[PDB]
Length: 225
Image (cartoon, rainbow, N blue to C red):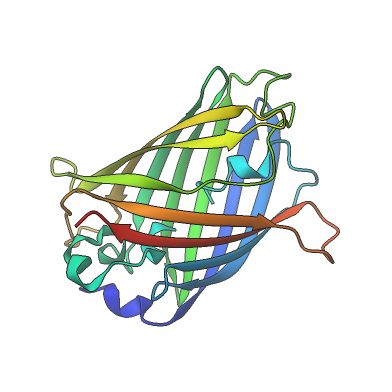
C-alpha cells in the first residue's frame, strides 16, 4: 500500500495534547520513535503546564496504532498505514465506571517525516475524590486486545475495547473505550476484516527528569486472522 512504505524504518514521533479535566486545564508533549517492524513504541511525555491533574495511566491509550505490527498474511487489513501520509481522525469516548469520561479528538499524520499526533482532550463528570482526581491509580498497566471492525458507511473503522486500571487497594478501575477512525484525505484506504491488536505496555520514570512526566514503552501486534 501507499503508506506501508513509510513505516519501513524507525519514525520520529511528536505528540501534543491539550486537555481540560473538570476545568483543570493542562498541556502535554511527547517525543519518541516508532518501529512498525517490531510493533515497538518508545515515548517520553512531559506535562508542560506543571503537575498533571490526572493519572498518567489514564492517557496511555490516548497517547499510534499505525505502529502495529501486522503479520505478513494480514497486511491487507492495515487501515492505519493505509491512511498515510494523509492521516486520519481518531475520535474517542472513554467512560470510567462510576466516574467521569474523557472525549478525545486527534489528528494523526506526517509532517515532513515526523509522525504527528495532535490531541484535544475534554473530560467531565469526574468525582473530585474519585479514583482519577484523587489519584488512586497505580503507576502500571495490563495487557489486552483492541477489537477492530469496518465502517463501510463511513469509510473508516470502529474500535471497541476496555482497559482495567489497578487501584492502590488492590481494586480495579474500568475504562470502556469507544473509537472511530476516519481518514483525512479523499484517498483510498484499506477496510479490514475483524481482528484485533495485542497490546503490551510498560510505564516508567526518568531518574534524571525532574519534571512531571511519563516514559512509556509499548508493543503492539495485530492478530485474529
